[PDB]
Each structure stands twice: as structure tokens, then as C-alpha cells.
Length: 52
Length: 70
Image (cartoon, rainbow over all chains, first blue to last red; front, side, top):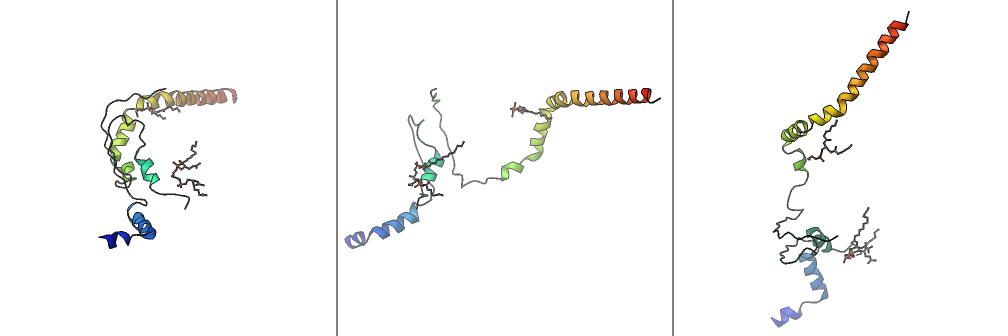
């Protein structure tokens, strides 16, 4: 388990995040005074950067 | 200028999980039925005066043309 854990480096983290996070679909569940929480398109757009 | 919360529950779907341009031509005959049935009064009021005035003007012009044409 320790070998598997410390076999994770920065490049591995980037590759896994690009596999799971970059431009994927989020699922939001909210309750309460959420009248100021941004809508779905906001999060879906925030899942990627246009600078890079 | 404040927001008035309503206590709703809203289910929404991703824009990439549902087709986009099919709803334009889906159920077209009923759409045209609505557009014509709920608006024929308005079209009559908008166009009737115009076509009536045009017909009156053409009638008057032709009658004067014949009368004055010796």
C-alpha cells in the first residue's frame, strides 16, 4: 500500500485529474438559502482553463 | 432590487445529455395551429386597414383617370 501511495507523483496526479476532472460533467446537490449559488453552466465552464 | 425566494425544488439536466435542435421542428403542425389561431385577430387588424386603403386609393385613382382622360 505504501509503495502504491508513494508511486504517485505530480505527473501521475495531473494525468489522473485530466482523466477525471478536465471538462467532465458535475452533479450538484444543494439545499438551503442557495439563491446565490451559481447555476450548472457556471460549474461546467469552471471545469477547464482557457489560459493554458 | 432584491430577490424573492420561493421555496421550490428544481431538477436540471446537463446540456450535453439532451438533444438540442430537434425541438424546433418537433410538433410543428400544432405550433402552426397555435400561431394562426391565437393571432388571426391581430393580423386582421394590422393588414385590413392597409389593404382596404390601398384598394380605395387604386379605385379612386382609376376612376379619376377615366373621368379626366377625355
